[PDB]
Amino acid sequence: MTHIVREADRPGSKINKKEVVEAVTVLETPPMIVVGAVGYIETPFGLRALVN
Amino acid sequence: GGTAGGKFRISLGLPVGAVMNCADNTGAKNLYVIAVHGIRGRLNRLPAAGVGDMFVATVKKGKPELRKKVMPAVVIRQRKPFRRRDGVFIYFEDNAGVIVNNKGEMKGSAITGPVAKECADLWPRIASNASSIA
Amino acid sequence: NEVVTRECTIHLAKRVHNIGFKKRAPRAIKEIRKFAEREMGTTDVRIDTRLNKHIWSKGIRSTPFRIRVRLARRRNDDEDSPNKLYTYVTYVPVSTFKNLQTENVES
Amino acid sequence: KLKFIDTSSKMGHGRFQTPADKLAFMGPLKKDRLKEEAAATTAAAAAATTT
Amino acid sequence: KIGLCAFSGYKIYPGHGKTMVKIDGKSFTFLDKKCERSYLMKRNPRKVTWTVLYRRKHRK
RNA sequence: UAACAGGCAAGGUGUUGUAAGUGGUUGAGCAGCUGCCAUACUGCGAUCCACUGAAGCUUAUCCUUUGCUUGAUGAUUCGA
C-alpha cells in the first residue's frame, strides 16, 4: 500500500477543489495467457460444463 | 444553529464527564461534560465530544452565578489527535470549550487562544470572536 | 572427497530469534548442530568445547550475532558407527565479520 | 488525477521519496565518499608496487 | 505542501507526522514521533547530533 | 548440472544517534611538580571537539543479486 495525494473533484462537499490524502493498494498484475475455452449449457439443475 | 455543508467524523476526545477549560471571559474557569448534543447512544457507550461539538456543561470552578447550573457549550480545542482530509493529524495542548447560547451565539465576547478550524466553520459567532482560527 | 573442511560464518541471531530469552541460547548448541547437518549432510556433530565456552560467553540470555566456525568432516575411528562420516565444529576467533566470504579450502 | 504518489520507505519512518533526494538533502557518507575514492586512487596506486 | 520539521529540520511530504498547535498559539509541524517526543522532552535541537540545526552550528 | 536453490557476503532500506582508538589542552581547577634563563610536560581532570550522520542492529515472516560456497541416492502405496 502507498497513499496518493490527489485534489478532489466533487461539487458541494467541503473537500471540493481541496487536495485530499487517500490510501491505495498495489496489485502486481503481469499478463494473462489465454490457454483454453469452456462451454456451458443450461440444465434444470444448473449450468453444465459441456465442452473443453 | 449554524451547520451548512457536512462535517467529517473526527476522533471524539472528550467523553462524559471530562473537565475541559473555559476560554470565554464569562468568568467560568471550567466546563464539565454532562452530555453531547447529538449522541443517540449505544449500550455501555459513553457520549463523547470532539472539536465543534455542542455539549451540555456545568461549571466546576468559576463565578457563582454560573456554577451549579446546566448550560450549553461548544468545544474549540482537544488533545486527541484527529485527522483532516488533507492528511494532517492535528492536536492541541489543552482541551477547551466556550459557553454558548442555545442558538450558537457565544455568551462572552473574547476567546483566549486558538479555535480549531473544524469548529469555526460550523459556528460563525465563535469564528467572529477568535483571534486565530486553526 | 569425504574429508572436507569449511570455514563458514553462521548468522546465529537469525536461528535463535523467535525463541524466548533465557532459552536463547542453549538452542544455539542445538542450532550449530542442525547447521553442520545441512552444509555437510552428516547427522553427527561434535561441537568443540571452545564453541561451548563461546556460546556461553555472555550468559544464557546473550549469545553472539555472527559466529565464524570451521566444519571438519572426518571418518569414525573407534568401532565405526553406522554412519562413517561425522562433523567437528570448531570456533574461529574472527575480529571483523565483514567481507569474510565462505571458503571451502582448509588443510 | 493523482498529484503525488508517496514512494518513501515503508520499513520504518521513511523520509525521502527517491534515493536521489537522500543524496541531495544529505551528503555523501563514509560510503560513496570512500568508494569513489578507493577506485580512482587505487588505479594510480596499484602500480606503486609495480614501479 | 512540504512542511519543515520543527525539531529535526527535515522536509515533510504529505502524510508523515503531526501538527501540535500550542495556545500561544504557535503551530509546530513535526516529521515523526521521534522528533515530537524529543520536543516535549525538551531536548535541544542544536545538541542532538543528527538534525539539520546541529549540522549548521558546525558544518558537521 | 545447477535455467535452480540453501548458507554467507555485498548493496539497498531502516532503527538507535555519533563506536573503539588516536590527537587536541576542549575544560571548572589542582594544601601537584617545575631555573638563574624569561621556561613546561604530564600515566592529574567530569565534560567537550576532530577523524565520525559514525558505529551497532536490520528477516529470523524486510528488499535486490554476475560475488564466495554447497547441492547425483530417499520411503510408502496406488489399475479403467
Image (spheres, grey):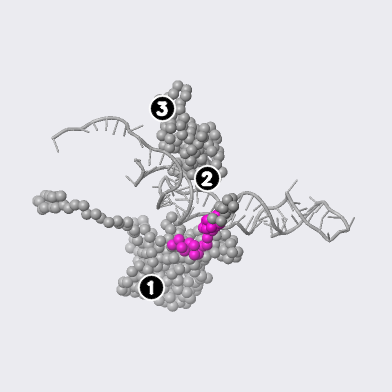
- Residue matched to label 3: C83
The residue sitting at the front extreme is D51
Residue A25: give x, y in percent of width and height: 34, 59
The residue marked by circle 2 belongs to what chain? C
The residue marked by circle 3 belongs to what chain? C
Q: CA distance from mark 2 to mark 1?
A: 64 Å
In front of the other: E28 or F55: F55
Q: Is disc 2 surrounded by few (<14), some (14 to 19) or many (20+) residues within 10 Å? A: few
In front of the other: E16 or B34: E16
- Residue matched to label 2: C97
Amino acid type of the residue that numbered disc 3 sits on in the rendered structure: Asn
Secondary element under disc 1, as helix, strand or loop, is loop
The residue marked by circle 1 belongs to what chain? B
> Number of numbered discs present?
3
Magenta residues (range): D18-42
The answer to which image quadrant residue D12 occupies is bottom left
Secondary element under disc 2, as helix, strand or loop, is loop
| Rendered residue at 35%/66% (across/down) | B38
Residue C54's disc number:
none
Q: CA distance from mark 2 to mark 3?
A: 34 Å
Residue C38 visible in the shown view: yes
The earlier-in-sequence mark between 2 and 3 is 3
Q: Are marks 2 and 1 on the same chain?
A: no
Residue B29 visible in the shown view: no
**Pair 1/3: label in front:** 3
Secondary element under disc 3, as helix, strand or loop, is loop
